[PDB]
Length: 211
Image (tube, rainbow, N blue to C red; front, side, top):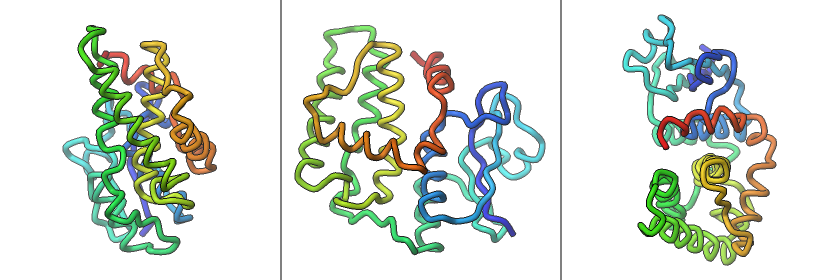
């Protein structure tokens, strides 16, 4: 059987890739391992029969490694892919697994903050400062010279942060964090990232109802 992945479509546009960063992580993994696969798009606001059969509870992403067993959760999927298709390796050493882990929740909290003295901007800045210090010493990626699984997780999250904070707050990752900027410049210009990133509008339109 085919290698398959179901991911989120744009709302009301079932043939346009949507803005799920967990879905993007899986797509990045498949692209970087140069595995042959089929991406199936699902508009979650109008879920088709065929999709409800595979994923009754309407979760994305869901993945089929070619054995007929659909599995959920991008943490699970990416490790199943690593175990099943080990070459080329994307293993991130465990010492660096939690690098950047608080950035995405801090971004969401700041995005929602209607209070400009509530400490959320500084909290995000401090996490970015920590990532900058990490990348300066052990970069250019989380695990040095080569892209690994942790980058394919964090990269989509930083892309959401960039696009959404600029749109809603006019806030950008400051350019004095030169190692963070080298990192996003490099990651976002990878062929796999260019191919799998959502259009900006489709990402803004997803966060819009949540702000």
